[PDB]
Length: 153
Length: 213
Length: 219
Image 1 (cartoon, rainbow over the protein chains, first blue to last red):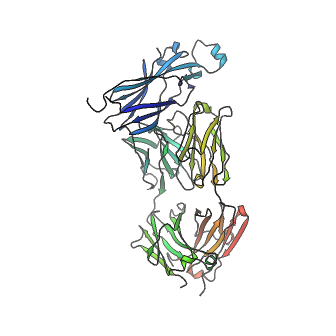
Image 2: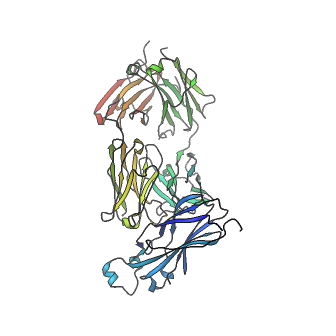
Image 3: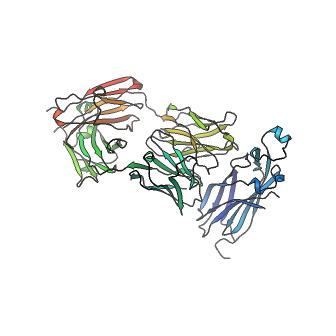
C-alpha cells in the first residue's frame, strides 16, 4: 500500500572505529500517521547475510520527523573466520513494520590494522585489538519494498 | 519531542530504607536510559547505564529497572553517603534529555516554622525601594507556602524565595521571602502581611505590620 | 587514568563570545563522543551538545542552535565549545563529559568551568537592617545585603564570635542583574536594646567591607 514510514538519512557516528566498538547510527525517519504496531530496526553482519548484530524496537511509532540513535553491539571475532577480519565486509541496516521489511541499507566496510607497519606485515594470529573498521558511509545501497501497513488493501 | 518526567521531586528517607525513583518517558525507549548522582559542588557520577547495567565501581545497592515507559532507580537499603540529587537521562531520541532531578533528603519529625516579618528600613526607603522580608525558621518538611498580602490583596510575581540546605545538625530548613515594591507604591497601602502554610501548622500563620505604625 | 579538564570560563557581556576547552587524557578522543552539559545556578542538568571527533558529526540542543559550535582537535586530544551571542540565561557551570560504549551515557565528567553572562558592572552591597520587633521563643533580627555584583559575599556576625542561630541564605539574581541575600540570627528577646548585633559583610570583588549595627527600631 501507500508508504507510512519512510527513511530519511543515516549518520554513521563513530567512524572509523575499533573492530570491537559498538556501532552508533543516528537514524532520521518520518512517520505520516499513527500506526498500530512496532518498527524493528536491525543490524546484520553479512561478510560472505550471515549474522544479526543487534535490533531495536520502537512502538508506538512517534508521528512526524524523528531522530534517534541506534547502538548495536559489534560482531564477535570468534563467530567469524579469520579470513574476514582484515578484508572488506558488509553491514546491513534494515527496518520492518509488523515483521514486514520495507527498507534496507547496505554499506561496505574496510577492516584494516591500526598502524602502517602492521598493515604491511600481517601476523599469522590476527590481533583483533588492533583492527580499525571504516564503514563507507558515503556510498550506501538503498533498497525499499512496498508493503501492507495498517490498511488491509 | 521527548520528555523525561521524573518523580518525585524531593524524597524523604532515613538510613536503611529501600528508596525508589521513577522516570517516565514520553515515548518508547528501548534501553538508552542512564541514572546519575550529583552532590552539591561536584560533577555528577554515572550510576547505571543502558536502563539496568550497573556502571563499574558503583555499589551494588543501586539497581535499574524498566516497566513499559517507566524507568526506575532502586536503592535497596539507603546508606548515609547516598543523600544526593539523582537525575535520569534518555539518549535514544534527539535531544538527549535529563530529568528534572530528585533530591533525597534526611527524614525527621515535623517541625513548625517560627515566622517573622521585617518592614523596610528608613535607609532603604530614601533610595527609592522597599524590601519586605518574611523569615521562616527551622522547619520540616521543606514543603511550605508563603503568600504576601498587601491590604488583603494577594501579591504575584513581585517576590523571590530562598532556601538553605538541610541543616547538618537538626535536619531542618529555613526560608526567606522578599517582596519588593517601589517606595512610591509602598506608601499607597497600610497592612503588609505574609501568610504561611505548612504541615507542622494546624492553621495558616500570618505575620503583619501597618506601615509607620 | 581517564580525566577531562575544562578551561575557558569566566565573565562576559550579553551578546559576546567565549570559547571553552576540554582536554582529554587517558583515552583516545576519536573513539568516543564528547558531550557538553551545563547547570544553571540551583537548577538541573541540561544537555547542550556533542561531537564524534572520528566523523566530525555533532548535535545541539534547541536552546543553543546557531549560537554554540562544538569542534574537536584530534591531535591535541581536545574538544572545544565556541559560544557566540551569549544571553544571560546561558549563565551556568559547563561540564565536558565523555561517552563510550554506554549508549551515550556519560561515564567521566570534568570538574566544570563557570560561565557568567551579564551587563552588570562590579558594585558593592548596600546593607540594610532587618530590625526585630516573639515566635518560637526568640526574636529574630538580620541583615539584608542588596544590589551587589558579582557573587560572592560573605556575612558574619560580631566578627565570627556569634555563629549559632545564624542562617545566611543563598543569593538571588534580581531583574536588575544584581544579587541580594539575607542573613538572619535568632536571639533571646531580652537582649534587644542591650546586646550589640553587628553583621560584617565582606564583598571581595569590589573590595568593600560593611559593618551594620542592627537595632530594634525606635518610637
